[PDB]
Image (cartoon, rainbow, N blue to C red; front, top):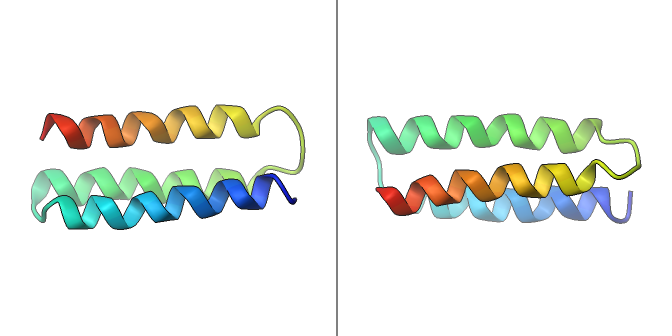
Length: 67
């Protein structure tokens, strides 16, 4: 998993930015969704699904901008 594992590394790095953006009912809920993201990459065995994971996380940060 030289490509899948790396994917997991980028997702967590973003996680730190979420907790640093604020701290409340909106901020706390946003990060919870992020946890789900980490679990999926772990399940990723090897294929063209890694691309789908990168797109989903992109949405999470987008919400951060709205707030």
